[PDB]
Image (cartoon, rainbow over all chains, first blue to last red; front, side):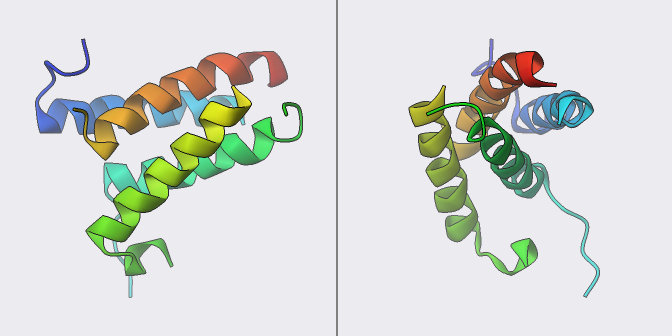
Length: 52
Length: 48
């Protein structure tokens, strides 16, 4: 279940999903939510070539 | 750059992308992102 995850577990789970999605498709380290935005944008860009 | 976005701008941007994905294929934005990433991954397997 998603809502039972702690905030830190939710971040980890998001990152794991991003890694899987990447297998398919000054300086500042990114947070999970920042990485999620990039990954969602990448997924949308690819899907829009095939769908709707 | 993505790090220039405030937390509100980041959340708003994430929900905008999720909305766009919903058209193609309670909770916080990060929870919604997890759901949307799982759904997008499942759909992208046929386009790898």
